[PDB]
Image (cartoon, rainbow over all chains, first blue to last red; front, side, top):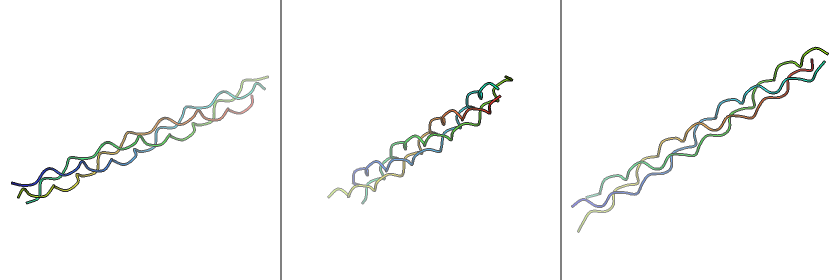
Length: 30
Length: 30
Length: 30
């Protein structure tokens, strides 16, 4: 009979970069 | 003969953080 | 005799997008 199944493959690669953060806080009072 | 390939490996790591966000709005008048 | 093991499996899928980036810098003084 054919042999046993092979090992699970290697982990997938790291995903793509996440989204930008949101805008920063308002600037100082004038 | 050889057995079948193993299954796909685990999912990869989450991707890296996204970039810093854009500048915030102006502060208001003095 | 039984056949040898099958080969290692294929790469896993890429992981998900990473986390959002940090909040942006403060806006301009008002």
